Length: 56
DNA sequence: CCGACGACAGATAATTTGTCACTGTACAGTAGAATATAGATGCGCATCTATATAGATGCAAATTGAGTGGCCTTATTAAATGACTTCTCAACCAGTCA
Image (cartoon, rainbow, N blue to C red; front, top):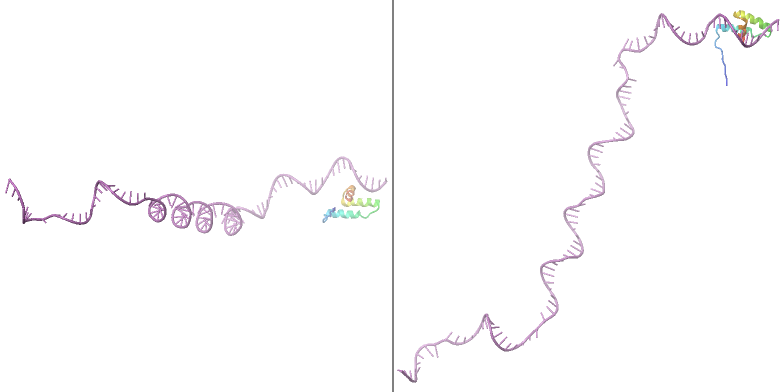
């Protein structure tokens, strides 16, 4: 048996979250995760735990 | 010391429900009805049939009247009755007598 889901055209908030996810797609260093997660919290204006929930 | 995940609490749009204002649309005589078909049922009229003959005919006893055929002692006499046949049926003159 088979299953899949595909996103339609993204909303503007989902576009911003796509740029944040792309900003968090590159790194390999724990220091750089901490830096880019905190800048992403500032870019989204959310808590650091909120950005962690978004990545998850 | 740094990073990731769970508990608890807090804030938030999606969902559902309710209320309110503006609006497209039906009310305007109208689809029960027309037109085929098959299939079964019933009344009428004809077309046979099977029974029922009484009249006519042929025949065979059953007398019935009307025929026809076959079988029989005889000769004399006498009487009686009834018949037949034959024959016959003159008239005056001549010789006695009381």
